[PDB]
Image: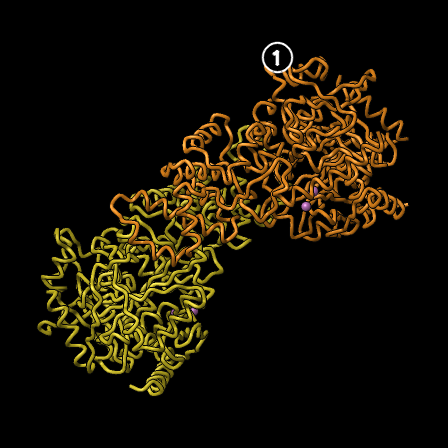
Chain colours: A orange, B yellow
Amino acid sequence: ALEDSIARFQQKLSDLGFQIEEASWLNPVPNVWSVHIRDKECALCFTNGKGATKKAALASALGEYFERLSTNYFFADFWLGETIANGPFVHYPNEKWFPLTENDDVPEGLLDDRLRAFYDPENELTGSMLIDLQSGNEDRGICGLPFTRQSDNQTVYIPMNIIGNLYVSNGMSAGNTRNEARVQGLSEVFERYVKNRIIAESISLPEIPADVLARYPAVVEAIETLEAEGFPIFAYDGSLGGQYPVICVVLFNPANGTCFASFGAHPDFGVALERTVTELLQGRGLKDLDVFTPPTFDDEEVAEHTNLETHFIDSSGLISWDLFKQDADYPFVDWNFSGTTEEEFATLMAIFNKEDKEVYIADYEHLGVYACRIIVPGMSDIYPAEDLWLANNSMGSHLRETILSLPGSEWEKEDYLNLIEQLDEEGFDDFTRVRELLGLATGSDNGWYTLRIGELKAMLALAGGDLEQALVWTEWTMEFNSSVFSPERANYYRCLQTLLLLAQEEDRQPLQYLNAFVRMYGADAVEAASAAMSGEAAFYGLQPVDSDLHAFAAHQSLLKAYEKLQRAKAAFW
Amino acid sequence: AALEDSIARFQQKLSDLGFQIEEASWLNPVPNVWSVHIRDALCFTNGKGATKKAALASALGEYFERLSTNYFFADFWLGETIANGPFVHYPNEKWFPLTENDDVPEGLLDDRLRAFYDPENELTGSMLIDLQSGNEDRGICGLPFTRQSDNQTVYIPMNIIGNLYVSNGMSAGNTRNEARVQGLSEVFERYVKNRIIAESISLPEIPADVLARYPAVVEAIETLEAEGFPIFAYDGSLGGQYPVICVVLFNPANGTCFASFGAHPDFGVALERTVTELLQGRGLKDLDVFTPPTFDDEEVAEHTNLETHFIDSSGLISWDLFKQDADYPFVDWNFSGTTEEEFATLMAIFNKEDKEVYIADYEHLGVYACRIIVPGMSDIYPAEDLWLANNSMGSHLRETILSLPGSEWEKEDYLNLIEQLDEEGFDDFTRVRELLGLATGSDNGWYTLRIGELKAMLALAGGDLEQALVWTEWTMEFNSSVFSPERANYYRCLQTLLLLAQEEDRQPLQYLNAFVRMYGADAVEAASAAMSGEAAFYGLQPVDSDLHAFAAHQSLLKAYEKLQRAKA
Ligand SMILES: [Hg+2]
Ligand SMILES: [Hg+2]
Ligand SMILES: [Hg+2]
Ligand SMILES: [Hg+2]
């Protein structure tokens, strides 16, 4: 059966043009496996899997692969270029574009009353904020994705922009049947929602009694081995008195005084438990358990939304000491929500119903595996709605063309300095990587890979002939990036910094030092740095970039992959 | 002397003293550049030269140099027994007991030195107690030096020597004058070094036709260049005044520079010694720990930058050193001759500078060695350090502190001690072993004990947990790095418990089992015992007046005893 699911996933992938390879494999303790898998064409296009056996792990990873392919999630941080942005469809043939209105209100056919209120309580939200990153196509309008509201059965259109910023990869799954995927999606919503409550409210949870654990000897053996290897484990029921199908497992690493909390959910208690333990060690051997944090008594810090966001991103957030209290805030419950997938779905939906929460579900068949994306506003959100104002991944796209065209530019000095001011008016953090802000797959072998806003200001100051500013930002750049620069790029900045420092020396004659600089930095770096100081060529190591990004090999590879999916969408619809 | 003969003569005299010396590590990083490292096991020196044999003779020379001056022992208190024995440093020495108004006793120094070290006349005898004895009752131990102008014996406090001159102006050799010439050369090396650096002087390059008189050095230099390391070779004579060379290396990988200074009456020998010191102790992969040049001349000139330069040559250098135009013309200088001639030539320089020279000679290990002092030139630390950074300050409290482990005093006593440490102005980061002069070894808490951590222990023993938390946080912040895993785990546990004690709405028993799982039972037991005041001095064994408690220190005193033997 498993050997057959695997084979069947692998065949459907080949048939889509995807050649996948197992990269790294781990069996750190008995009954715990993880595997990493990627595109041969494309190493950044990967998933991971976990399980009680080698085969289970691989099936997990291929499952996740279809989950991420079906939701376009590999591509969610990137702009897909001018051609795709004007093609027949961008995300799905299904999608609906709502062009902007004169007073820039959110167009009439998007969302529903509940959602408008949830995302926009102050009624201060505008349509131009909602342009999806992938297209950036303001003229074409707001791309909305169809979801099915479960209370009735109505299709609701939700801006991709809102999905991408607030829900990220949460509530997504693949499965063998439509409902099976739905159940996993819903389970995951509960996993992350309950996780956040446990953490943010500093809840002391009830231990799973040893007689319950002993129904699951494979997990027990995994646990005991971890203990035996120097890692105390706490196994907790996270149901909050039987409300939710959630387990929590925590690991201590006494070597450095830290803890690491893993949360899993499934209608079957045993399976939830196994999943929680297998996720704990996913991607990690026993030498990789040293990057976590000590518990804390500062509950206010534990509760901060950013701490929860961190926990979602890498599980390296703060946990309260209270989670480990002798006495629990809830009795243990030997819960169970299992049944047929149809039963399971209804059981989980009933929970959402008693909570008075609407569920929105999109289903995808088009790669020949069932997959869903589920949104439960007030429960499935990873980032709070104000992020549509403060941390929108689309903000930054009006400037893309300007910035992509700085290499080779030749504007008047004033223009470049105004751009520094624009970047400050628009509020960009000096540490923001420019590639993330604009959605570019750069590759590692150019200056764009490591270009943050602060460095960009330095280049702009150089091109605009303001050397007081250029020095400020060049220092900033050296302080916060020499680490990651190639040796050639770091040498260039070291040279440049020295030259900018020298230019502020009112009692010193530059020609006295030129020979010494050539010996320290080499002639090319000196030539290049001096050219940058003249404003001649400030955009050191930045090649110019077209609208379809032919300049970046990485980004071309990304789009070759994406085209395979655009193909499969066209067939299916 | 011939090298084979110096080596032989040295190795024999060492065995005869009871010293088994072992060539440890050897380097020949480029042609005609050798260094060697030499051990008993923390009793060590290094040597440098153009050949393997030269390096070894250098190292053994240095070994006798350091043995004869007691320099291996300079940072350490030698215990109550030695401090009350017949003599501490040398049978020669003279003890000057303190006076009622606590003036500096009459028979020490001379008028010129009193005035130099104590211009304000603000100096007291109790400041001048040597670190090795700490014996205030016995008085100020003074060492006899010979004033060269008229040959009079002058007694100089060991305290002043140890704090201001450290290892500068010391050498050994085959003849008396050979040692003296190297000593005097060294005084010029370090004095001129400091001027070049502190005044941001641009020096004149040595022309290639002069370098070519010395093909061995040239080949060394060209290899370094070829390996990616630009070299500047400078005349440091300051227009032919001083017999000094400067060689600077760039590491373009890093953007850093490393400046080496050598001195000898023979230009060729000074040049070789400078290049050979540059790479001493270092292969070509070890040239990455230095500093970029700078335009901040005020920083370059700071005495602490010069002190750093003396300690590890990792100080700041001005970009000006590398200016196209030099502040002095190159001079093809030369002061060489017979040893006897060389000594006189160097002495004449000091005479034209109106500087007195004081020299102590030591024959007692069968090798000629000297220590030379030229106030105003050989000083490494400025005279005000006798007030501000005296290595004896901290010795009145030694007994107290050594007896804290196991102590059962009043809570009040311990807390007053925190106040004392603050009144006396000790830096929280001062390692206690340095402050008291203890060779601890690495496997105990004393190795890593800084004043801040000590305050933590004192607060714990005195039952002040608000303070104990403060200092325990401080300790974790500035030391978890170097602690053994066991010691770091203890502090992590303790910190957690102190934090818990500040929690007004939490019940400690709720967390105990979890703490035991994280920290282990011993650490929990221990940390709780420390919190009760029961046993605050975690991992600190108690220490007797002769330091039998520290194996390291016992080894140090076994070595010292060999020298004390040789002194009679
Ligand atoms: Hg790629
Ligand atoms: Hg990819
Ligand atoms: Hg020693
Ligand atoms: Hg030793």
Residue under label 1: A102
Q: Quadrant of ligand 3?
A: bottom left
Q: How many marks on residues? A: 1
Q: Residue at x 10, y 61 (%)?
A: B112
Taking the image as shown, residue A519 lies to the left or right of residue B87, namely: right
Q: Secondary structure at mark 1?
A: loop
Taking the image as shown, residue B216 lies to the left or right of residue A344, namely: left
Percent position of residue A193, x then y: 70, 28
Taking the image as shown, residue B173 lies to the left or right of residue A340, namely: left
Percent position of residue A293, x then y: 59, 41
Subunit that carries the residue with mark 1:
A
Q: Residue at x 33, y 87 (%)?
A: B5
Percent position of residue B387, x then y: 23, 52
Taking the image as shown, residue A394 lies to the left or right of residue B459, namely: right
Image quadrant assignment for residue A142? top right
Image quadrant assignment for residue B200? bottom left
B361, A421: nearer the viewer? A421
Figure quadrant of the C terminus of chain B: bottom left
Identify residue type, mark 1.
Answer: Glu
B134, A294: nearer the viewer? A294
The residue at label 1 has a CB less than 8 Å from ligand 2: no
B399, B37: nearer the viewer? B37
Q: Is residue B190 above or below residue B53?
A: above
Q: Is residue B68 visible?
A: yes
Figure quadrant of the N terminus of chain B: bottom left
Percent position of residue A375, x then y: 74, 25
Q: Is residue A267 visible?
A: no
Q: Residues within 10 Å of mark 1 (few under 14, many from 20)?
A: few
Q: Is residue A448 above or below residue B249?
A: above
